[PDB]
Amino acid sequence: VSTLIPPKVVSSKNIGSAPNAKRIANVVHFYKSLPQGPAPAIKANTRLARYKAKYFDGDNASGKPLWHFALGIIAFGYSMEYYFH
Amino acid sequence: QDLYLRELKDTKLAPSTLQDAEGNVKPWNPPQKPNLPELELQGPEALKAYTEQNVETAHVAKESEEGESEPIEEDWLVLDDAEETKESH
């Protein structure tokens, strides 16, 4: 004889179907993350890492590193050809 | 005049032994002395409801009932129906 109780029965009722499914996905995606640009890790110098933080950086990454690599390759090849040819 | 005594004795003799005093009937054969208080005693009784409304039967109707001390069973039934109604909201 008791009336229905919508706001009293919300323990099992969630927000539709998709919103409750994505609530767990969105609650923790924003929890454990850097606030703003933390840990840049820019500093690196290990020849390969020296190239990474010197010319191979993605801020520009223009053809200048490629031209420098080609210049070094042809400089080595000149001596190689002198040895061979 | 003559009528001044004749009609007064007319309306004081026959009505005297017709009603009020309630004894005998001289002017006409049918008597209303045992007709109006005895035969007509059930007159309105016949016209109205007898043994039901004239006696005002003390009909003791059944007292208002309730959920008959229903346990938590109806509580969780209400929970279930509310949940299935609110699931599609």
Image: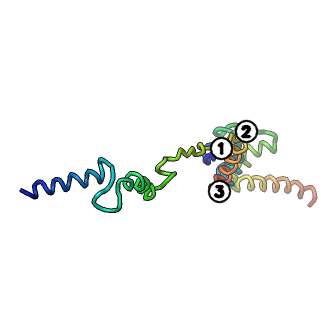
Where, quadrant-wise, is the C terminus of chain B in this rendering?
A: bottom right
Provide the secondary structure element on which disc 3 rests. Answer: loop
Provide the secondary structure element on which disc 1 rests. Answer: loop
Camera-nearest label, 1 or 2: 1
Q: Position of residue A39 (x, y in %)?
A: 70, 37
Q: Residues within 10 Å of mark 3 (few under 14, many from 20)?
A: few
User: Could you tell me how far apart the alpha carbons at marks 1 and 2 are, in whole angstroms?
Assistant: 72 Å
Q: Quadrant of residue A45?
A: top right
**Which of the pair B39/A39 is nearer the observer?**
B39
Q: Position of residue B14 (x, y in %)?
A: 25, 55
Q: What amino acid is labelled 2 in the image?
A: Ala
Residue underneath mark 1: B67
Residue underneath mark 3: B88
User: Could you tell me how far apart the alpha carbons at marks 1 and 3 are, in whole angstroms?
Assistant: 29 Å
**Which of the pair A45/B53 is nearer the observer?**
B53
User: Could you tell me how far apart the alpha carbons at marks 2 and 3 are, in whole angstroms?
Assistant: 50 Å
The mark found on residue A41 in the picture is: 2
- Residue at 70 percent across and 56 percent down: it is A63
Q: Position of residue B24 (x, y in %)?
A: 33, 53
Q: What amino acid is labelled 3 in the image?
A: Ser
Provide the secondary structure element on which disc 2 rests. Answer: loop
Are the residues at dot 1 and dot 3 in contact (C-beta closer than 8 Å)? no
Could you tell me if residue B85 is visible in this image?
yes
Q: Position of residue B61 (x, y in %)?
A: 57, 46
- Residue at 26 percent across and 50 percent down: it is B16
- Residue at 93 percent across and 58 percent down: it is A84
Q: What amino acid is labelled 1 in the image?
A: Gly
